[PDB]
Amino acid sequence: LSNNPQGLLLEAIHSAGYSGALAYPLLAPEAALNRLDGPSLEEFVAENYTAPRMVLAAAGVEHEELVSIAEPLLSDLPNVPRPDEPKSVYVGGDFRRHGES
Amino acid sequence: LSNNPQGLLLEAIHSAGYSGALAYPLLAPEAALNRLDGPSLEEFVAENYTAPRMVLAAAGVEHEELVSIAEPLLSDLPNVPRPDEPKSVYVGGDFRRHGES
């Protein structure tokens, strides 16, 4: 990872200067990587990948064709109440990490 | 070295609070470890191991025989005067190092 300090510093700024939601890291630290698992992914997907939060966007496709091929594949998903988005406050200070010379 | 967090914290206090002579690390960081050489050590010793900085202490040794044995082996060193004491100034400081634990 250290080969690109820009991405590392963006992640560091987000983690430092946000508290919960935006502070959740994006590159999966080693402890999280060890803890992660297939059933955990299954549960996460099944809980979050729901119909009221899915957009299928085409760039060079006729709309009639796209909808006629996509409705028999997505119309039977369960209708969920779209649970609310997380909160995050900005107050945040300094992150400092020492590496190469 | 990470298995002894107490010594690490003490060294971190010294490094992050002092500035200069007392902030110089005691445990040879990676780059300096790579760079050190036999001639470097030899020059350091030759410049810093002078007579006004030699104390031969003995615990249960008679003074007469001790001096009779240690006079020929030490009286011929050059009389280099003491250099100026390495001055350091104390400031505040915050050190913070994430890790697995």
Image: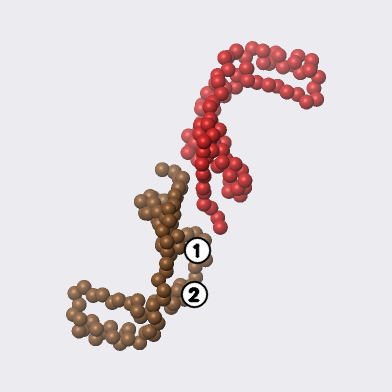
Chain colours: A red, B brown
Which part of the image, by quadrant, shows the C terminus of chain A? bottom right
Give the camera-side residue of B87 and B97.
B87
Count the marks: how many? 2
Vertical side of B72 occupied by B95: above or below: above
Which residue corresponds to the image point at 58% horizontal and 17% vertical from the top-left?
Answer: A82
Secondary structure at badge 1 equals helix
Q: Position of residue A79 (x, y in %)?
A: 60, 12
| Residue picked out by circle 1 | B32
Which residue corresponds to the image point at 18% horizontal and 80% vertical from the top-left?
Answer: B62
Which residue corresponds to the image point at 44% horizontal and 49% vertical from the top-left?
Answer: B94
Residues behind callouts 1 and 2 on a single chain: yes
Q: Classify residue B73 by image quadrant.
A: bottom left
Give the camera-side residue of B59 and B90.
B90
Secondary structure at badge 2 equals helix
Residue type indicated by callout 1 = Ala
Which label was assigned to residue B39? 2
Residue A68 left/right relative to B55 = right
Residue type indicated by callout 2 = Pro
Earlier in the chain: of badge 1 and badge 2, it is 1
Q: CA distance from mark 1 to mark 2?
A: 14 Å
Crowdedness near tag 2: few (<14), some (14–19) or many (≥20) residues, C-alpha within 10 Å: few
Chain containing the residue with disc 1: B
Q: Classify residue A67 by image quadrant.
A: top right
Residue B38 left/right relative to B54 = right
